[PDB]
Amino acid sequence: NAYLNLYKIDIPKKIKRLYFYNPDMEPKLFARNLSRVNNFKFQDSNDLVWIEIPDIDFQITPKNVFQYKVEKEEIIKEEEDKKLFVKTLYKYIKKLFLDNDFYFKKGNNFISNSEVFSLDSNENVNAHLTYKIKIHNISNEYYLSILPKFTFLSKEPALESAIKSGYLYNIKSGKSFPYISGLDGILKIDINNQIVEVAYPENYLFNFTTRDAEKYGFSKEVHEIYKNKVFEGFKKIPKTLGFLNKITNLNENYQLKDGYKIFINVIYKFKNGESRYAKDVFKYSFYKNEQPLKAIFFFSSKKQFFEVQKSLKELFHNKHSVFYRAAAELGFSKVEFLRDSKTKSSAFLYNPEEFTVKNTEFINQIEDNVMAIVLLDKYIGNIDPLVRNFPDNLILQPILKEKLIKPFIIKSYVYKMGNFIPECKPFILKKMEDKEKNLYIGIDLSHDRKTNLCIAAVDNTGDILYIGKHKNLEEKMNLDILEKEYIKAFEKYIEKFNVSPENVFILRAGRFIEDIEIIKNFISYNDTKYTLVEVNKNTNINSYDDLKEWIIKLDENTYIYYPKTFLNQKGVEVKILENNTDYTIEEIIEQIYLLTRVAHSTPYTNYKLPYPLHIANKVALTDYEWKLYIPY
RNA sequence: GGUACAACCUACUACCUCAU
DNA sequence: ATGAGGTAGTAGGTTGTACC
C-alpha cells in the first residue's frame, strides 16, 4: 500500500476569536507584549486586544493573563470564511514549530536545531533536518502535507566559524543579511546600505551558495545526502514532530483508497514497430521520414577548424562513423553536405563576437531546410546574438567543441535535427493516435506591474500549430487578448486539418484568477466541447515510496502525477476545473500525462509538463532563446 | 549551447495589518 | 508617499546527476 505524506487535521473547522481587556496597560503595548511572548500575533481594537486561534486548547502566555479575558467570544466557521481558517491555521502551525525550537524559513520551511549532523566532506558544515508544511483541502476536508528536506548551515556562529560566506541567517529573526565584517569581536551586516553592529554574533549562522559548496568540496555530498538520507526524514516524523499532535494524529498515515493510484504506461509508435522506450527510435526508425539530411558547417576560425578537424573528420566525414550510422537508423533518405560553387569547401566561417557571417550568394540562395552545424568554443554568457544574427531561413544546430565523444550525445543531436524537420514525425503516442480531433493549448502568465501572456497549441502527434506571446501591461481587456489568441490558434488548427476541433483542451499554469464564465462562454458557443484544466508544478505531496510514472487521485476533481526523471521525484497537480467533453475525468487526466510524452527533446530525457504548457512557459521566459529548443 | 531536471542562495513583485 | 511587521508566488543564475 502506497504511503502518502498527508495527515488529516482532526480539529473543529471553526476558528474562535477571543478578547482580552487590560485596564492597567495601554492596549497596543499589551498586544505587542502578548504577540512577542506567545510567538503569535495579537491584534488591538479600540479598547480591547484580540487573537484569532483554531478551536483547540491554546495556552496563553503568561497564565496571569486569564484575568483580562472576557466571556465574549466569536466563532467563525470554516464554511463562512475558508481563507481565515487556513491562514489562522498556518499561524498556529508556525507558533507550534517556533515553540518547539524550530527555525522559520521562507516558504513554510522549519529547520531543526537539535537534529543536525556534521558533513563527512566538511566538518565545519552542519546539515539541519528541515520540514516543509502545507495545508491542502481535498474531499471537503483539511489535510497537512509534510516534506523532509535539508538545510545546510555552518556548525558554529560566524565569528567562531572557520567557513565564511556572503550572507548570514538569523536563528531568532529568520531573515538573512549580507555579511560585511567580523572584525574585533563585533559582526557587521548590511540591511538600503545601512551597516550596524548586531548584539548577538552567536545567533547568526552561515548559509551557502552552490559555488561555495563546490569551493569547499561538500557540493556532491549535498546531493548524496538528499537522495540518500531523505527516507529517515519520513520515518522520524511522529517522533520529531509529535508536538503537532494537537491538530493531527501522526501515527496514523494517509491511506489511498484502492483504485485511486494508477500506473500509466506509454508506448511509442514507430515506423516498423512500437516500444515503451524512447531510445528504441534507433531500432525502429522514425514513424515518418524518408527525407534527406542536408547540412553545412560553421567554424569560429580556421585555427579551431584545424584543431577540431581530427575528431571532426572521423566523426562526420567517414561513412562508417556513428553520425551516418545513426542518421540511417532514424530513416533519413541520405546524408549530404552542401558545397558552394565559390570554393569546394563545405565549411564556413563566422566571427564569435557578433555571431554574424558575411552574406554570401550560396547562403542567400540556399534551400529551405538545412542544418547549420555551429561549433562553439565554450559556453557563452548570452546566446540571443546567435539567434538574432544568424541567417533567418536556416535551422540552427549548435554543438560545443568540448562535446566533440559520447555516442548518445551525437545520437541526441541527430534526433534534434529530426525533430526540427516539419515532414518528419519521430513518433506518435499509441494512445494519442485517435486524438486527432482534440486541440491542446497551454496558457502561461509571467509577471514583471505589467504582466505578459503566452499560449501554445499542439495536436496529438506533437506538431506545434501556433504560439502566441504578448508583453502588454496588466480583466476584460486581457480576456479580449485571450479570445483573439484562442481564435488565432483555432484558425491554425482548422488550417492544418480543414476541420473545426470537436474537443479543445485548455491547460493553464496555476489557478484561474481570471473570469471563468466568459472563457467557457466564448469557447463553448461554437458548439465545441471544452475542458478547463489547472496545472501546478508546485505541490508538496510526496512519499518515500517511488511514485514515478504514477497518477494519484486525491479527490474526484484533483489528481497528481509524477513524471519519470532520474532525480528525486516531484509531483505535478492536475485539476479538471470544468468539463463538458465526451471524455471522462480519468481519460482527460491520462491525456494530460500523455502530453508530457508527445514530444522528446532527446530520446533519453523526459518533459515534466504537458507539451503545450512547457512550450508556453519556455516562450514566456525568454524572447529569443526558446527558438533554439522549440521547432516553430 | 545534444538535453531533462533536482538542489541552492539571492532578489523582486503583489497583497495584509499596523501606522508617520 | 513611506516605512514597519507578515505571507505568497516566481525570476536570476550556479552546480549536481543522468541519458550511454
Image (cartoon, coloured by chain):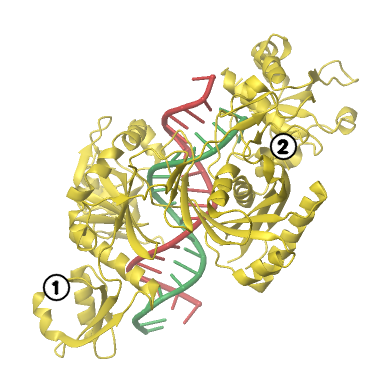
Chain colours: A yellow, B green, C red
Residue A401 in view here: no
Give how far apart the Cα atoms at labels 2 and 1 are.
Answer: 67 Å
Q: Are marks 2 and 1 on the same chain?
A: yes
Decide: marks 2, 1 in contact (CB < 8 A)? no
* Secondary structure of the residue carrying numbered label 1: loop
Question: For the residue carrying disc 2, how many other residues have a C-alpha within 10 Å: few (<14), some (14-19), or many (20+)?
Answer: few
Chain where mark 1 sits: A
Q: Quarter of the image for the N terminus of chain A: give it.
A: top left
Q: Is residue A418 above or below residue A507?
A: above
Q: Which mark is residue A61?
A: 1
Please provide percent x and percent y for residue A476. Answer: 66, 73
* Residue for badge 2: A354
Q: Amino acid at mark 2?
A: Glu
Q: Nearer the viewer, mark 2 or mark 1?
A: 1
- Camera-side residue of C15 and A558: A558
Which chain letter matches label 2?
A
Kind of residue at badge 1: Thr
Q: Quadrant of residue A245?
A: bottom left
- The image shows a total of numbered marks equal to 2
Q: Could you say where residue A106 lies in the image, as x and y percent from the top left?
A: 36, 57
In the picture, the quarter occupied by the C terminus of chain A is top right
Q: Earlier in the sequence, mark 2 or mark 1?
A: 1
Judged left or right of residue A286, residue A572 is left
Residue A477 sits in quarter? bottom right
Element type where label 2 sits in the image: loop
